[PDB]
Amino acid sequence: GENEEIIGGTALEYNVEAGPSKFLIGTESGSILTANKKLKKPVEITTRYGL
Amino acid sequence: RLLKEVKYFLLLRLEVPTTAKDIYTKAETYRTQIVALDMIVDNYNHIK
């Protein structure tokens, strides 16, 4: 939206069966984000697990 | 520790310090300037 706060990436998870697409990232605030790397747009933060 | 303390107060919102905002805005500029400074400082040591 407009509210952009930079929150510390406390944990990162990556697996073969998930593939090189998805990177599952945990934060200080308690939420969990997912960064799908693209050859298109340099990076995208798709899902927001527990907003 | 003060520079880190101010950031976590903004994250929890509740309340904020008086006239410590000016230190926190420039905070980023100090963390470039301290590294930048360092650069030279080192070199001096290993130069001496």
Image (cartoon, rainbow, N blue to C red):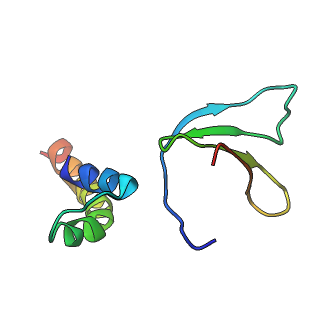
Depth order, front residue of B8/B35: B8
Depth order, front residue of A47/A10: A47
- For residue A18, what is the image quadrant? top right
Depth order, front residue of A2/B35: A2
Q: In percent of the image, x 49 and y 57: which residue is there?
A: A6
Depth order, front residue of B34/B14: B14
Q: Name the residue at the left extreme.
A: B48
Q: In percent of the image, x 86 and y 33: which residue is there?
A: A19
Q: In percent of the image, x 26 and y 60: which residue is there?
A: B15
- In the rendered structure, the answer to whether residue B26 lies left or right of residue B47 reads right
Number of callouts = 0
- In the rendered structure, the answer to whether residue A49 lies left or right of residue A8 reads right
Q: In percent of the image, x 23 and y 69: which residue is there?
A: B21
Location of residue A15 in the rendering, given as x and y in whole percent from the top left corner:
78, 26
- In the rendered structure, the answer to whether residue A9 lies left or right of residue B42 reads right
Location of residue A32 in the rendering, given as x and y in whole percent from the top left corner:
63, 41
Q: In this view, does B43 lie above or below A16?
A: below
Quadrant of the drawing holding the C terminus of chain B = top left
Location of residue B43 in the rendering, given as x and y in whole percent from the top left corner:
23, 50
Location of residue B34 in the rendering, given as x and y in whole percent from the top left corner:
24, 57
Q: Is residue B2 above or below residue B29?
A: above
- For residue A3, what is the image quadrant? bottom right
